[PDB]
Image: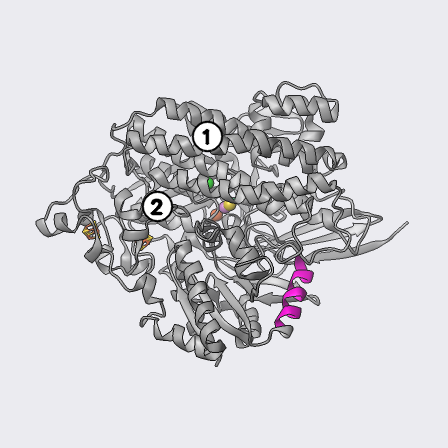
């Protein structure tokens, strides 16, 4: 990219998120986050990093949205809570009127080129939707479907996702759009999503079947303490067998470690995370 | 000469999480304030019924900026509840994991959250548009230094997360801290890798970050004269320096009404009159805490509970810890206080109460604390023993309780767990931004930031920049505050 090149507008809305999906993106190595922001996208609204504030920030987003109706990308971080008329997530106020996450997704969702549901919360409900919750935390695709909103959704899950999954999915979509236009390009992206809406370049391979400890698993050689790095981690709770992600190869944080080497995989990219992956520390 | 204007800011940006601030301005100054945390998830109810060991993963998702703090408080609570005796080398390894995120978090806060309060960024989103009269006072050269350092800091904070991940597995959301210690013994090779990254971070902190905070501060000397609030602080202790549980890098204490006092955790109570929780749950200590949402309750304005310490409204964070502990100032700080401010100082309290408890004083304290943490990490790198075991594997108890106390980058954090029938019966969290960004208590006394907003200047109601500047000095994360 260049400072002077074409960069599509992006709005980043946080619902019931922890900001971990923003922080993981800040950790991108190649390209760096500076290059992403200055050369790849135009991040027009993002409450954690943007210059302006309050109603002015909301109105700026609305002005860009009108100019780029049908053409902006909408990133959602966190789940969307529907209970109590949306009151468990208020994202802004304008004109003396509060804006819930429910309101915001109904407003901007219909007019986005595509919605990128970043993180397991947005993709599948995640921890805010888990047993013991009471906010009506809802995944993006289900919320949009329930409200008749047909805009395409791409899920980029993980808790958090790896930065390469987020940036790489953006790069994949922008490439498809460059070659085919918006509708043709999004059709090419949909073709490479699995049944859970995830791009197969990043989520098309199972961790366990590619794990360096697979021989130990097949031999029944299991570590009894976390600090034994020779044995397989299955008895300690590893969920690699049920998890579709490429962590075994790209690893984390500049390649310095990953969950299976350090401890166990907790299946964080899967639609049943956390309840279907718990307890974390037994099989 | 002017009357009232009431100003609402939602979202407050360049913080973590969902915050609305509403201030009453009369005659050019804030005279009242209300802070509203507008998003709730309910971790304290989600946790119930689970295997207690799961908590040290679940709790980190309270907040992806400070997950190591929640991990630490959780494993300390579980250690106590399980009777787990963490090996000495695991104690040190935990400190290396967590300490690296203090560096990440303070650098993120000053550059990527706060610096745009004083620095104009490049002419493209997300750096524009902004207030037409943003009160950006820096020369062309110093503004450019701020931008150049913002950009460099993006790399430095990423390197800090590589440091976290070396023994923590990944970041955000470490895998490497569990009940009983740390899951990966440091090897000689990975300790080399941690030290090489740490040197780059140290050089940035010493040469760029600490100097730029004092230098920008010297162009905003008026910002040391506002934001005092109650001038009352809390520290609960953090970073155990031996296995006794009695010695910590930051020692506990309370400061209020000009007096140092001991910290007794039994004096914490959480009030809810102005919070969206059932009225019957008001006034509980965390060991008996309850979390019953009431989003329609009349008069309430926040999902943050109102914690009070023996009735006092206190603040937490770097200022609190540095004031309570009064360490020596960094060599850089001493020199620049003299050269740019005409101040002769040796220890942190030599700034004086008024300047320390101020908008810019909180930025200074955070920079000084970052430098202070460098020395702690260097010490742990000398103390750690490559190859020595870092974990024990304790059985889950049927019935137990435990409390973990630490200091997150933004201030005091505790987690309390009660186990019954080998499952979580109650789990209560009292976090840093809870102490700072809470609403009024049942007696009408304001939270720390609400009170620190009193007196903030708003000489231009169309460009009321100092309201959110004050808020950002406290480095709020509303995910932590509400959970
Ligand atoms: S259970 Fe986990 S550690 Fe064992 S082979 Fe499978 S993915 Fe690897
Ligand atoms: S190894 Fe498992 S828990 Fe770790 S990031 Fe990959 S999918 Fe998530
Ligand atoms: N730092 C941090 Fe998070 C907050 N506030 C906690 O505790
Ligand atoms: Cl932290
Ligand atoms: Fe709490
Ligand atoms: Ni936090
Ligand atoms: S945080």
Majority SS type along the magenta span: helix
Residue farthest along the left direction in this orientation: A219
User: Is B338 or B472 nearer to us in this picture?
Assistant: B338
Chain letter for mark 2: A
Q: Is residue A78 visible?
A: yes
At a point 70% along the width and 44% down the height, the residue shown is B453
Span colored in magenta? A53-65
Chain letter for mark 1: B
The percent position of residue B219, horizontal first and vertical second, equals 74, 36
**Location of mark 1 (residue):** B199
Mark 1 crowd level (few <14, some 14–19, many ≥20, 10 Å Cα): few
At a point 63% along the width and 25% down the height, the residue shown is B333
At numbered mark 2, what does the secondary structure look like: helix, strand or loop?
Answer: loop
Where B126 falls versus B415 (above or below)? below
**Location of mark 2 (residue):** A255
Mark 2 crowd level (few <14, some 14–19, many ≥20, 10 Å Cα): some
């Amino acid at each position: 990219g260049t400072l002077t090149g074409e960069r599509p507008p992006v709005f980043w809305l946080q619902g019931q998120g922890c900001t971990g999906c923003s922080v993981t993106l800040l950790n991108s190595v190649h390209p760096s986050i500076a290059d992403v922001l200055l050369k790849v996208i135009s991040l027009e609204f993002h409450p954690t990093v943007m210059a302006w504030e309050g109603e002015h920030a909301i109105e700026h987003m609305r002005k860009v949205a009108e100019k780029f109706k049908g053409k902006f990308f909408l990133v959602i971080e966190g789940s969307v809570p529907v209970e109590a008329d949306g009151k468990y997530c208020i994202i802004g106020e304008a004109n003396h009127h509060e804006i819930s996450m429910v309101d915001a997704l109904k407003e901007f969702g219909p007019n986005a080129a595509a919605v990128l549901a970043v993180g397991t919360c947005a993709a599948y409900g995640g921890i805010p939707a888990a047993e013991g919750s009471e906010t009506g935390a809802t995944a993006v695709s289900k919320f949009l479907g329930d409200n008749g909103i047909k805009t395409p959704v791409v899920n980029i899950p993980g808790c958090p996702p790896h930065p390469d999954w987020i940036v790489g999915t953006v790069v994949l979509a922008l490439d498809a759009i460059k070659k085919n236009g918006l509708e043709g390009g999004l059709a090419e992206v949909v073709k490479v999503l699995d049944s859970d809406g995830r791009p197969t370049p990043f989520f098309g391979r199972n961790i366990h079947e590619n794990c360096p400890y697979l021989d130990k698993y097949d031999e029944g050689v299991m570590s009894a303490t976390f600090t034994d790095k020779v044995g397989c981690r299955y008895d300690l709770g590893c969920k690699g067998p049920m998890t579709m992600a490429d962590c075994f190869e790209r690893k984390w944080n500049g390649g310095v470690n990953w969950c299976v080497q350090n401890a166990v995989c907790i299946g964080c990219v899967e639609p049943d995370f956390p309840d279907g992956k718990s307890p974390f520390y037994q099989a | 000469a002017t009357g009232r204007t009431t100003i609402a800011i939602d979202p407050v940006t360049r913080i973590e999480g969902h915050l609305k601030a509403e201030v009453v301005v009369e005659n050019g100054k804030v005279v009242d304030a209300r802070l509203s945390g507008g998003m709730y998830r309910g971790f304290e109810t989600i946790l119930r019924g689970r295997d207690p060991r799961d908590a040290s993963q679940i709790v980190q998702r309270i907040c992806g900026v400070c997950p190591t703090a929640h991990s630490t408080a959780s494993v300390l609570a579980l250690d106590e509840a399980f009777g787990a005796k963490v090996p000495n080398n695991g104690r040190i390894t935990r400190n290396l994991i967590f300490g690296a995120n203090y560096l990440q978090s303070h650098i993120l806060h000053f550059y990527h959250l706060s610096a745009q309060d004083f620095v104009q960024g490049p002419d493209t989103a997300p750096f524009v548009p902004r207030f037409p009269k943003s009160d950006l006072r820096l020369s062309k050269e110093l503004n450019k230094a701020g931008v150049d350092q913002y950009i460099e800091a993006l790399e430095v904070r990423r390197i800090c997360h590589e440091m976290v991940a070396l023994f923590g597995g990944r970041m955000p959301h470490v895998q490497g801290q569990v009940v009983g210690g740390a899951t990966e013994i440091p090897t000689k090779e990975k300790l080399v890798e941690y030290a090489a990254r740490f040197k780059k971070v140290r050089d940035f902190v010493e040469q760029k970050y600490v100097p730029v905070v004092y230098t920008i501060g010297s162009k905003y000397k008026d910002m040391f004269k506002v934001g005092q609030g109650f001038k009352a602080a809390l520290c609960v202790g953090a970073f155990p320096l031996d296995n006794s549980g009695k010695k910590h890098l930051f020692m506990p204490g309370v400061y209020a009404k000009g007096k140092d006092m001991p910290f007794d955790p039994s004096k914490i109570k959480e009030y809810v009159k102005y919070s969206w929780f059932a009225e019957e749950t008001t006034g509980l200590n965390y060991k008996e805490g309850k979390t019953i949402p009431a989003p329609d309750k009349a008069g309430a304005y926040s999902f943050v509970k109102a914690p009070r310490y023996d009735g006092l409204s206190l603040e937490v964070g770097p200022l609190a810890r540095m004031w309570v502990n009064n360490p020596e100032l960094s060599p850089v700080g001493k020199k620049l206080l003299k050269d740019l401010f005409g101040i002769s100082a040796k220890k942190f309290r030599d700034l004086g109460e008024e300047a320390a408890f101020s908008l810019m004083g909180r930025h200074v304290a955070r920079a000084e604390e970052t430098y202070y943490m460098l020395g702690a990490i260097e010490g742990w790198l000398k103390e750690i023993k490559a190859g020595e075991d870092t974990v024990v594997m304790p059985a889950v108890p049927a019935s137990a309780e435990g409390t973990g106390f630490t200091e997150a980058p933004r201030g005091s954090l505790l987690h309390y767990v009660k186990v019954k029938d080998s499952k979580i019966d109650n789990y209560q969290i009292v976090s840093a931004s809870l102490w700072n960004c809470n609403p009024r208590d049942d007696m009408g006394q304001r939270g720390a930031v609400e009170e620190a907003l009193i007196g903030i200047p708003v000489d231009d109601i169309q460009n009321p920049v100092n309201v959110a500047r004050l808020i950002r000095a406290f480095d709020p994360x509303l995910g932590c505050a509400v959970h």
